[PDB]
Image (cartoon, rainbow, N blue to C red):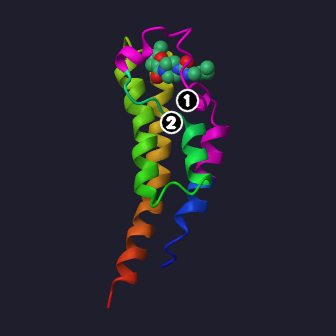
Amino acid sequence: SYDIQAWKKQCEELLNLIFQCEDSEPFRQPVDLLEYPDYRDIIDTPMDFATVRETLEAGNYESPMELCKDVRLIFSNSKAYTPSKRSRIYSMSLRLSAFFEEHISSVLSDYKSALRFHKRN
Ligand SMILES: CCCCNC(=O)N1CCN(C(=O)c2ccc(C)o2)CC1
């Protein structure tokens, strides 16, 4: 399965599944600084799933590893901003992270395998 370009549509489909998850609602658009006035005191690099989808559709990811780094930043931002491990929005992030990691692992493996096959000779 050595298609070097296959990751892009695989990531589009996984983003569609994440947008159908009720657990993604807080992560679909940038944090409102009006409602969370201290957000940018703590978070130096905002990230949301609409920004990830737009970056992918612009052709501004070279690899699924770059997309994976931005999605993991959504989750690390939620962990850094939460006042408690028992917060609603943080708990939604942990379930969504487990779902994302379960589905991205084959996308990364197949891409890296395809690149190794491309350089085989
Ligand atoms: C305007 C449409 C939604 C915008 N998102 C949004 O407001 N947030 C999601 C990110 N965030 C957190 O990760 C987080 C962790 C713990 C708590 C209370 O928030 C801050 C809130």
Locate residue 78: give its quadrant. top left
Q: Which residues are drawn in magenta?
A: 13-42
Instruction: Say what amino acid the circle numbered 2 marks.
Output: Leu
Residue 31 in view: yes
Q: Secondary structure at mark 1?
A: helix
Magenta-colored stretch includes residue 115:
no
Could you tell me how many numbered marks the image carries?
Answer: 2
Q: Which mark is residue 96?
A: 2
Q: Which mark is residue 27?
A: 1
Locate residue 115: give its quadrant. bottom left
Give above or below for 39 relative to 104: above
What residue is rendered at 63% in x and 54% in y?
Answer: 13
Instruction: Pinpoint residue 44: horizontal percent, then vertical percent.
Output: 37, 26
Query: Label 2: few (<14), some or many (≥20) within 10 Å?
Result: some
Q: Is residue 74 left or right of residue 32?
A: left
Q: Are marks 1 and 2 in contact (CB under 8 Å)?
A: yes
Q: CA distance from mark 1 to mark 2?
A: 10 Å
Disc 1 residue lies near ligand 1 with CB under 8 A: yes
Q: Earlier in the sequence, mark 1 or mark 2?
A: 1
- The secondary structure that dominates the magenta segment is helix
What residue is rendered at 35% in x and 18% in y?
Answer: 42
Magenta-colored stretch includes residue 28:
yes
